[PDB]
Image (cartoon, rainbow, N blue to C red):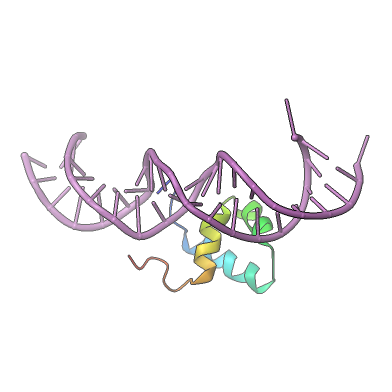
Amino acid sequence: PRGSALSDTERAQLDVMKLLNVSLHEMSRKISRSRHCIRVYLKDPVSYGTS
DNA sequence: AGGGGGGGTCCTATAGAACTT
DNA sequence: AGTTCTATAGGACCCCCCCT
């Protein structure tokens, strides 16, 4: 895609951050990733990588 | 028309795998 | 090293707030 897929770490952060109720926008800033990936992934982290 | 904050959409090249030399 | 492939990351464009 336009960028690399999410690393286990990145996705790991994302999981915690969500737990912390961080905002999408802050999340991106935090790990320098588009809201887009972040969004999609959190909507279903499992399904990520299933293609 | 900016900076900051929150949230969408959705086009579109390309990551990265599978393959072929 | 090149090919060929397509689901997907980027980020464009949108909505709404308030302000050194």
